[PDB]
Image 1 (cartoon, rainbow, N blue to C red):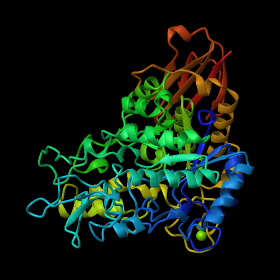
Image 2 (cartoon, rainbow, N blue to C red; image 1 turned 90 degrees about the vertical axis):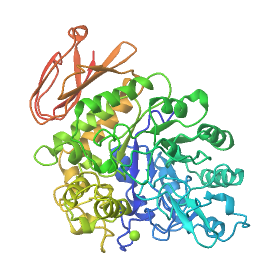
Image 3 (cartoon, protein in one colour; image 1 turned 30 degrees about the vertical axis):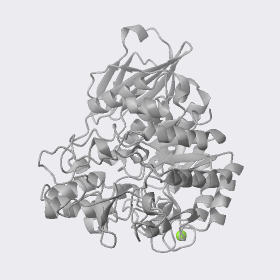
Length: 559
Ligand SMILES: [Mg+2]
């Protein structure tokens, strides 16, 4: 199946390329940069959402599923982009955002008017408690209550995300049919599949039970906010009614997923999705359940990363399918978050790339990952993300569960905007992203980190990623081999083995700044190896003992 063999490039289009000079990346901009993505080697593009939206959550609040936001272009531009992607032998996946809509969606504008409105039950309306307070103690992912009051009708509406993102009612068959109609519209026009936003959220516990509480917080985000009792029923219906009718790829953003939930989503026999994104490997550098959420930061712990990625490799080794990512439009640049983004930036980028791309599953490259883009030094007032603005107010100002200094530090590590400053094309004004004024400033380091210099440098991170993708296409063990964690207890080295029809692929990466030592286990000492890729000058190829330099990475194949 082409999706098992694919390498996906994720574009965040408001920040990819601005062709028309208004500082906002657009769909003609994407068209003009397709050749770049094909030369890198990705064969699937996932486009973050371009549908009409007031941009409260930068597109993830959709006000019209069947039209583009005007700054992206029109539907004609989107149709042309589909054609251009196809002419290049590539596939295009769109972002399906159907847990919620914008509150400016016509459905919601209607729903809120009156209880007798035909769109009332498209959304999730509940009575206040007797004292007027919220139906229950559920919180929003973007701080505060998950419920907002409507004075006109005397009820609260549910929003797991912003108050401008009211949740749809999947108990209503008309809502499910509307979704299906949206899916068909775009698939009939050549969309090759969907990344399904917050897909773990679509089924609610319709009794709306309160969480138990520790009194550490007023509003709680927990186990009711994902993996609802009808979740898989709904996805199986979506497959029967839609997905089974097209040659398509699906990847779910599966909030709340663990390895068993992943099997329910991804086992081919269940006729649901092809693969999901989990957050468990992204969760390893927060406390489990602080009131401060993801902002309660822990240092990078390689043993935790090994444990989690291994659990996922083994759990979907022979059933289901993994995604492989360290970056997207919600995560900081991995090298700044967990590594060295200064003197060892190249080595470190390549090392994280090698660990990820040597595993079983479909790899995802986030725009700019391939050139080693880094987190930004911009001051807090320059950040745009509502998540940060809301968390500052709740955690720092109101509840005082974090100090200002601790919050700023956490934002500088994990803010989503580190992913959203514009793609860095060259060393000219605004890194060549725009001839105008960009919607957010370009990262201050762009003159050193950009496509132009990367393509001039045979040692670039770019050429490394290009090579990793070629190797995947050349060596079917990379796609189909199994997985075994080696030297498991080593606190610096991430090493593992894949095996497929008598061949072996050995991946050894020092994820640390200091020297380390890899010694192959006894059963591999008499293997002969050919080095497929390394991020340091020398060979290769006596892999039974490797004195590892900082961030050294090597992949070998048995011969
Ligand atoms: Mg523009």
